[PDB]
Length: 207
Picture 1 (cartoon, rainbow, N blue to C red):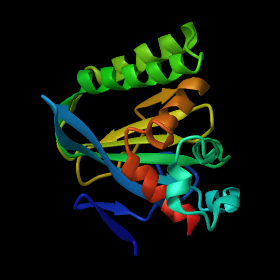
Picture 2: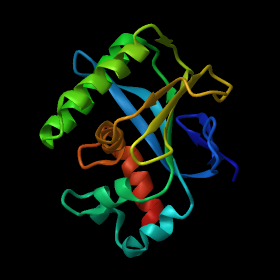
Picture 3: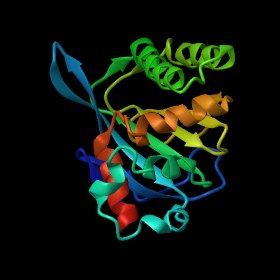
Picture 4: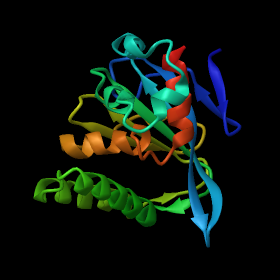
């Protein structure tokens, strides 16, 4: 259709991020989590969008089982992440959170990924501090939208809006290519914080 339910939240099947020139299709969706004293709680609804052509860049995976694709060392993750097409994630907050803890968690997770790949130099460290600082003054209540748009492979346009509206302008830009790739790896990599979104995406490509 034109609208899909992700955790009873409406996600459009097609979407142009703020200030973008290109219509992106909904490839997969899922959720991310949080915990309180080991109890698992649903934190956000996620939708992963990309230029329709991403399907053709990944033709070679057609007809493989989804379970093959998401398995470690399959190679699919990196080819998904590196597909030379525009991509975006739309996040809809399910459990409200202050902006500092969210930005610090993001920083922590992106650092871990960059460190684990020997890519965490002073440039990446500064870019992450400034990303965390962007979020620190905001509150992210239930229903808030966060859009990350990979307009170029080395850049991420970050935009935010209240429930019911998409953002009109870009609020923040990530200018570091390694951070930009780490942010995609956060959602689509072997150690993804959202296995459900990755499983949804792989299904969509394999079929």
